[PDB]
Length: 28
Image 1 (cartoon, helix red, strand yellow):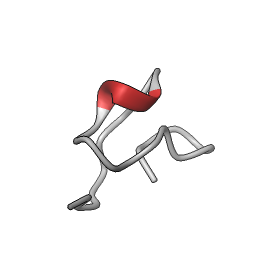
Image 2: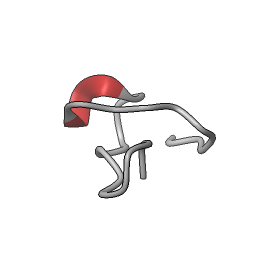
Image 3: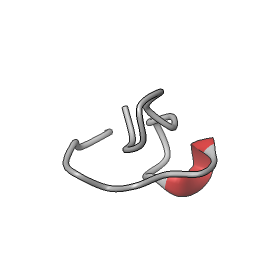
Image 4: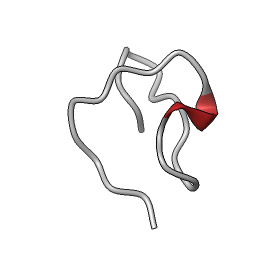
């Protein structure tokens, strides 16, 4: 599964397996 919260990203893998780097700053 893919949660959601203010978690800054730089790459897809940044977040938990399922999410992508949300085009804004934080995961999406």
